[PDB]
Amino acid sequence: QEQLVESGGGLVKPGGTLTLTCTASGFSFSSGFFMCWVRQAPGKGLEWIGCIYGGSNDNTYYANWAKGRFTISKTSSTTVTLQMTSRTAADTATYFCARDAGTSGYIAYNLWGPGTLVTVSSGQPKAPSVFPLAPCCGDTPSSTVTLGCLVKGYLPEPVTVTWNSGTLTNGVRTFPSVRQSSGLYSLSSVVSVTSSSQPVTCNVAHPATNTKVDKTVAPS
Amino acid sequence: HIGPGRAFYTTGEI
Amino acid sequence: ALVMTQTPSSVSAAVGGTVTINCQASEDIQRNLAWYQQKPGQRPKFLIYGVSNLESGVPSRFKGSGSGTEYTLTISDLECDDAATYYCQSALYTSATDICAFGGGTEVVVKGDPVAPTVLIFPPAADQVATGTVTIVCVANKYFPDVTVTWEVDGTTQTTGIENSKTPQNSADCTYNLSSTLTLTSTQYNSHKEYTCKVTQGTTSVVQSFNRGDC
View: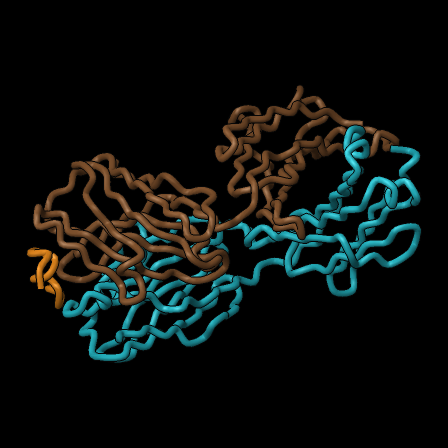
């Protein structure tokens, strides 16, 4: 099935320049549709940037505020680029690759990627520390227990967490991150399990530092 | 029915 | 240029009820109106194109209407899976800046069965304290409506060094989850005994504690 995947987001110093890549699978850059970019600052709304035509007339069309800082190009039959120069912290956002299918001559963004996060910042990257979350050792064991991992003190976002290499998904709660005063983010992931359900292992991955941490967690 | 953009989505031009 | 304006910035209704969002266009858009649903953390989901044409898999109870300047999305038989922000989008095909304009978004909150939270407190792992800071994690799991968290160290109200974050409403039962995290220096932490998380839901409270020496 058709799928989009954005690529290239990360840290960038203010004024530095970034190039993001979008990659389509399951369909090809014909004509009759556009490839578009949309950004969304954290908690803020959807803000269109620009499109580019599928037919070989690679017509590029930008929003008023956008041209001169952003540029969209067909880097291959299957990859589209957007290149940007940061200025303000408001350039920090999630960047979405979308497809306007133009169905029946109406606007129709019927395909979206997961988006890639650009962080405008002067700060140094930092990989997270991972600590086990287990109930107090001085408690009495129950037939049922909730364990977890605290993923503390990292930059930039994101971090991803899975349990038992994605084998364990029932009863998993992974909380949205929070920015600390230091500028580093934190989040927790918890999983509820039968006290007999073997070891449980959280898998923490922080691509920006090429890090993966596995922490096997047990009670008390 | 047809939408008021069928020409634009066909050409990429306007 | 073309500006879209979604009117009620937020809105609530019960499961099985009905809610209405409106979106205002600057000019005559001639029914060129798309809707999207976005839950926090996820990409937008295409719902409707051309004021009312349902994309496949989108159930019928999403009624888009309107003409000219005023369009309406009407969600009926509301379900917890509808908890999200909805965006209108339209286009004028004459200028470079009007190929796309998004509305500002409307939050939709769904009221389900009230469920009282279960509270867990997680004392710091044995290796945290040797780093100079200690982070205590408390969770209020699977609850509706919202709760209030309160902290107490040896009986004293704590308000600093606390961050909270709430999971968005669960698609199946509308419930929230909350983590409340308390951070202190290792020296602050070793100078106290009893750490307390207090989660309040109206007239009910659940309180979990540990004593540092025992964990």
